[PDB]
């Protein structure tokens, strides 16, 4: 049986994309740029801060100095950190708390494999910290998803090989990173987005220990 589960944060445990979106929107409004809506935000998801800011500036064809660019970037991050102060256990995705309990009761290791720079803070606010055996530090890994490094680090941090692990992800890059790490992916979302070759569930309420066991046995 698998010995660990490696969790992405956004789109698996909770929604942080909402707060990034709101923070970019509020920045854009604050400097008179229109058009930062949820559709446009698709071009900002999982993209660096610089790239995002550049794309938002490119809407209005607005020019800034290096000093101004830096300050804008900081203001968005400050706004994001303010907005996540509201995170609570009410923000945990369905099925996830029960899954963590059940994994823990079965001595299966639980690790976070997220690019979130606020991962520990977020898990604390959601009261999940006690379930986690490690949180992979994205500052200590060389390359981001779809590189496998973050999943490798998460596995190793709990004393397992990625080949002994299931990885849970909602993104194409993340599924690819899981695959390349050696772990078994189980996607959440749509096969139209994540591929027909992996097991995918429609939402997180389908991530149960029994289902994960069945998937493991069938691989
Ligand atoms: Mg995700």
Image: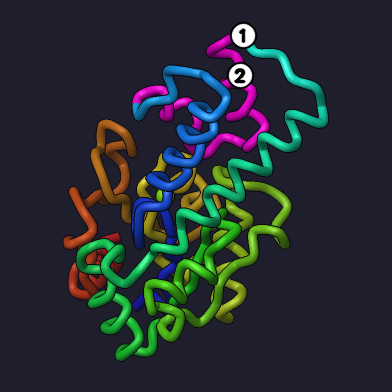
Residue 30 position in % (x across, y down): 54, 30
- In this rendering, does residue 106 appear at all? yes
User: Which mark is on residue 123?
Assistant: none
Residue at disc 2, secondary structure: helix
Q: Is residue 103 above or below residue 166?
A: below
Q: Nearer the viewer, residue 38 or 5?
A: 38
Q: Which residue lies under the disc numbered 1?
A: 61
- In the image, the residue with mark 2 has its CB under 8 Å from the nearest atom of ligand 1: no
- In this rendering, does residue 214 appear at all? no
Q: Image check: 53 left or right of 59?
A: right
Residue at disc 1, secondary structure: loop
Q: Is residue 86 above or below residue 64?
A: below
Tell me the magenta residue range. Answer: 39-60
Q: Distance from label 2 to label 1 (Cα)?
A: 6 Å
Please tell me in which quadrant of the rendered image residue 209 appears.
bottom left
Question: How packed is label 2: few (under 14 Cα within 10 Å), some, or many (20 or more)?
Answer: some
- In the image, the residue with mark 1 has its CB under 8 Å from the nearest atom of ligand 1: no
Q: Is residue 143 above or below residue 117?
A: above
Q: Residue furthest top?
A: 61
Circles 2 and 1: CB atoms closer than 8 Å: yes
Q: Which residue lies under the disc numbered 2?
A: 57
């Amino acid at each position: 049986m698998f010995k660990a589960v490696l969790f992405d944060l956004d789109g698996v445990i909770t929604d942080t994309a909402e707060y990034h979106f709101r923070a970019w929107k509020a920045l854009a409004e604050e400097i008179g740029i229109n058009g930062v809506d949820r559709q446009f935000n698709e071009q900002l998801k999982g993209v660096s801060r610089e790239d995002s800011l550049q794309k938002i500036l490119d809407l209005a064809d607005k020019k800034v100095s290096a000093e101004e660019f830096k300050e804008l970037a900081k203001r968005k991050n400050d706004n994001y950190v303010k907005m996540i102060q509201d995170v609570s256990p009410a923000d945990v995705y369905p099925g996830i708390l029960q899954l963590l309990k059940d994994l823990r009761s079965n001595k299966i290791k639980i690790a976070l494999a997220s690019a979130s720079k606020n991962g520990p803070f977020l898990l604390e606010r959601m009261n999940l910290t006690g379930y986690f055996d490690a949180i992979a530090d994205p500052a200590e890994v060389a390359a981001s998803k779809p590189a496998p490094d973050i999943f490798i680090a998460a596995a190793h941090a709990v004393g397992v090989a990625p080949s002994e692990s299931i990885g849970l992800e909602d993104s194409q890059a993340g599924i690819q990173a899981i695959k390349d790490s050696g772990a078994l992916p189980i996607g959440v979302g749509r096969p139209e987005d994540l591929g027909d070759d992996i097991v995918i569930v429609p939402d997180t309420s389908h991530y149960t220990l029994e289902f994960l066991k069945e998937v493991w046995l069938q691989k």
